[PDB]
Structure formats: structure tokens, C-alpha cells
Image (tube, coloured by chain):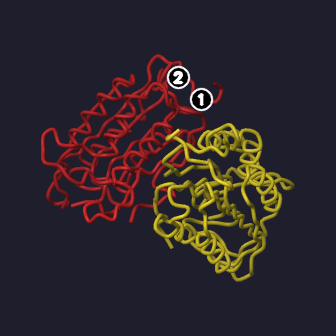
Chain colours: A red, B yellow
Amino acid sequence: PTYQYNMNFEKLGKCIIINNKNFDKVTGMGVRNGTDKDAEALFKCFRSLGFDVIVYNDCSCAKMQDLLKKASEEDHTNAACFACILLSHGEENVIYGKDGVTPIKDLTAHFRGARCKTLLEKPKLFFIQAARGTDTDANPRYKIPVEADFLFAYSTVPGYYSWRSPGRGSWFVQALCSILEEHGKDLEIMQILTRVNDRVARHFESQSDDPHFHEKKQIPCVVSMLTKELYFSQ
Amino acid sequence: PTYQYNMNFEKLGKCIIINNKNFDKVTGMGVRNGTDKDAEALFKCFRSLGFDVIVYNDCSCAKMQDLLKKASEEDHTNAACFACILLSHGEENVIYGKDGVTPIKDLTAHFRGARCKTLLEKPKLFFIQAARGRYKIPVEADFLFAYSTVPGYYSWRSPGRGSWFVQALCSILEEHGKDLEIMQILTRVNDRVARHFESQSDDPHFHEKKQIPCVVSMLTKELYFSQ
């Protein structure tokens, strides 16, 4: 209890959702079908958790940057924590805007104590569902502001198939939401996210020798600098 | 239940401890005093958790590579998990051998799912303590890294005692090691070294060095060293 973040605040905090579905053809990236379904789930889910959710769509690089900076400049004094979720295309250390590419570390750095005193000693959660596109990544969180109270959940797992409407949705993202609804108010985040890792990991039906399940195995990556346990409830 | 790793085996598992204190001149690196304090602290600690701890000192890059290559090649059918602890100098995805540098991905390379079936589905723990300052260190299921600083940072202590990180880990483990889940333990460590920080020096035109341990997790279940 002196081992978990103080959640006795006016409000839980803000939850920013960047939903990037469409991209300029100059980037070579295609439509991210299924992203809308993830967005829909996430916002409903975090809303339920008690977050004040904002959803942005098809943002430019400048758009994402000004977006987060401004947020890192608001007064988070009456908030317990802060959450940001990025849904787009990604390449080692980068995420796509519709017009180009920006480094994730710049997107998150805005919230480092130095430049956001109002969220000091407060958990800052980043859930990224990027994925190379149209054998995993690295760990040295250098493409992340290594500072206390920061937590990243990077996917990279692709939303592989999809006919359409409402689309199936990304695995990682749907797992997250599913668990976060059923247990959002009982489990600690690392519990939530560990259950998530497992769930997407199982989607690759173990190590099947069947020429139908043989593929690029992937799993989310959880990076924690949290200094206390995180519960969203009472 | 199906939410925690199955610890029902004869042994907890192997725990290799690489303790590189002295380095050849050709690397331009200096003695890591206090790492012997760390190494021992870590030994009695992990040994007490239940690991079969073996410590190796001032290893060469070749030595560390082979050391871990052989470990992966052993039979872990009666093991619940595996754990490697590295104490040394580091810069990024690479740690220091006593005769040069070797990257991290290589140490964990031969443990990936396919390459070590016996340890498959079971947790491979890596506790790293690098300092000072190849590439990409993969992301496989059931691996967990606990970096002392973060690829290319600092870690300090008190002339006579080991790193704050190590000391924190041993103290917490040597107290809740058997009742708290791995992530809890590590979080408290994160908090412990935090409190120790944002120091006093007096060359305000030199004192930068900070520190926040960090935990990369690909675990698929909760981890307890008990039951």
C-alpha cells in the first residue's frame, strides 16, 4: 500500500489515442485495416477504466509531436497517471505519421520529469502497436526516455489477416482490451500485460509443425521503470 | 495457477555469475572494485533462493561466449528456469570481456526457443550490471532482463560496498524472494535505487550521471521462486 502509486486524485488522468489508418503513398505504407477496430476497443476500454480519452486520427508527424508536447504542458496535478497509445506503422525506433516518420523517443521524451513536473512520481504508460510492414526488435530502451515511472508495451506483432468490417483487430490490442476490461480493476499492470504477452503468444498455437501455423513468431515487449505497483481501482 | 510458471521440478535451475573485475590493458578499462562484494552478495542470495550458482571471474569474450553456449547445451528437463548474471563494464548492446567486448544478443542467442527446448516454455532470467559509456538484442517469449543502469549509463555505490542496484536486489530478494512475484521484487528495486538518486558533486559542469534500473519483460506467466 506504500508499495503502490497513490491514486487518490480528482481524476485518473488523460488517455491519448493516436489512430493512424491512412498514409501518403509517398511513404510506401498502405492502409491499416483493423486499426479502427482497435481504436474503438481501446477508447471504450480506457473510458471504462476511468480515463478521459481523446482520439486523434491519421496524424502527420508534426501533428503527433505538437500533440504530445502540448499534453506534456498541461497541469496534471489533479491526475493519478497518464496514458498514450500509438497505432501505426513502425520501423526500428520509429513510428509513421501519414506524411512521414518520427522517432518514438522524441514523442515520449516530452513527459520526462524535467519537462513535465506535474506528472513526476506518476506512472506514464505508453502502449505502442506499430509493426514493420507493406526477427524481432531491440531491448536497449534507448528509443524510450529511461527515467523512473515510465512503462512501454511495444507490440510489433502484425494484424496479419482481415476480410473487413468491423475488421478483426490487432491481436495484441484486442488482448489488451479484453484483459483490461475483465480485470482492469483487480490486477496490477504487469499482471495485465503478462497475461497479454501470453495471449498473443498463444495465437501462434505453440510451435506447430503444421504448414498452416508455421510463421514468424512474435511477442509484445514490456519495458518497466515503474517504482511502485499500478492499480487503476480505488 | 495457469497464471504462474510451473516451479514443480527437482531444481530451481542453473545460475551463472560472470564476475569481470580485472581487464587486459588492450581494452583501456579499469578495475571494478566492489564487484567482489556484489558477486558474493549475489551468490549467497541466489543460492539461498535455490539456484545452483557457479561464479566465473575475469572472463574473456571467448570464455563468456562458450560458458553460456555450454549452459544452453545442458539438459534442463529437471529445471524450472535458468538465470545468468553479468557484472562488468558495458556500453550498449555489448558488455566487456576481460580482453575486449562481446554483445548481449550473443549471450542469449543460444537460448532462444528453438535452440534450447529443455528450457523452452520456462523463464530465462538475465540480470545485467554494465557501466561506463554488435546490435539488436531480440525479443523471445519467456526471457526477462533486469539492467542495472540501461545500455550506456552509470552505476555507483560506496567504496566498500557493491552497486546500489545489486545491494537492492539482494536485500529485497533476501527478504521477499519467496513471497513476491518477480516483477514486484524488481519494481521495489527500481524504487530503492531511485531514492538513492540525483546527487551532490560540485563540478556542476561535470556531474550528469543518473540511474534508473530497467526491466524488459517477455514473461508469459507470473514468476515465484516458491512452491
The numbered disc on residue B141 is none
The amino acid type found where label 1 is placed reads Gln
Compared to residue A17, the image places residue B66 above or below, namely below
Instruction: Decide: few, some or many residues near mark 1? Use Cα within 10 Å; few <14, some 14-19, many ≥20.
Output: some
Residue position for label 1: A4
Q: Residue at x 72, y 73 (%)?
A: B29
Q: Position of residue B107 (x, y in %)?
A: 58, 70
Q: Is residue B37 left or right of residue B185?
A: right
- Asked whether the residues under the numbered discs 1 and 2 touch, taking CB atoms below 8 Å apart as contact, a structural biologist would say yes
Front residue of B78 and B94: B78
- The residue that appears at 35% across and 24% down in the rendered structure is A52
Horizontal side, residue A164 vs residue A233: left or right: left
Residue A7, disc:
2
Q: In this picture, is B18 found above or below B63?
A: above
Q: Is residue A67 above or below residue B205?
A: above
Circle 2 marks a residue in which chain? Answer: A
Q: Give the x, y percent position of residue A157.
A: 33, 54
Q: Secondary structure at mark 1?
A: loop
Do the residues marked 1 and 2 share a common chain? yes
Which residue appears farthest toward the right when viewing the image?
B160
Chain where mark 1 sits:
A
Q: Quadrant of the N terminus of chain A?
A: top right
